[PDB]
Image (cartoon, rainbow, N blue to C red; front, side):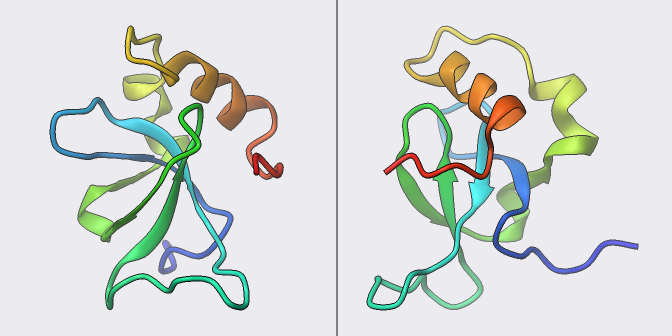
Length: 93
């Protein structure tokens, strides 16, 4: 059975106007800006941008990759597909 989301989990993350996007739940480093309550820090692969999202917009990667894990024209998307599959826990800073 599923647990709550935790740092390191791999997802497709959905935002308004963008396709379901390969991403991970990030850790929050000491000193770093914390998310709002009930929100997680989401690191988007390829673009390397961060946004704060709740679970309604987070689709676990294993379950969802057959649907959402296909090339897209959008900037950074296909780079992001490579990262999530090949080195999803690397430093992209």
